[PDB]
Image (tube, rainbow, N blue to C red; front, side, top):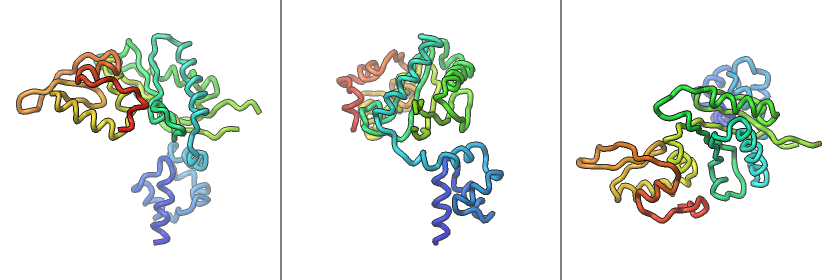
Length: 242
């Protein structure tokens, strides 16, 4: 009812999940001013999200993402030019506007065999914080950071969502592919790969075999390699709609 209407609203809050939204309803928490008067019952994630509820509802325009992307890439280069960083999402595909920034990062020092180098990711975050670009943290793991940023005002911009994922180097390409989308695209490409005798996922590309249940990741140094494996002309991100 006009109350379910309530769980509907809550959930619009980053951090506020259903189960999580449900309880808040059992506490008599419904509107947003409810929430604001009730910070104490929210985790840090939900707090931030509530803090920036509005801003989060706005889309990001390419002219913006561009600048965003330059800040991010230039910082990372300064720490260590060996670092690889790519901004994915529709944006990579030439989208005109976006919902958030999604950065994928890797480093030759870190491969799927290592598996433990938080510093690699932290360092960048810190750097971003120090520059005044990242402004808050929603959560921050050993492999993934979820926060908020904002373009430097010279006078102001909304706060935007940003995520930085640390992926091993030997799995990066597949990963960039993957986060590049579109969804259909992925689907069709995985479909084709299969016809060719291969299985792809966001981490690897592996040859099939008898009965099907088969594998052993092939080496990938770039997106191009994946396409070559399945022998399809290479598709630039823009031609990736489907």
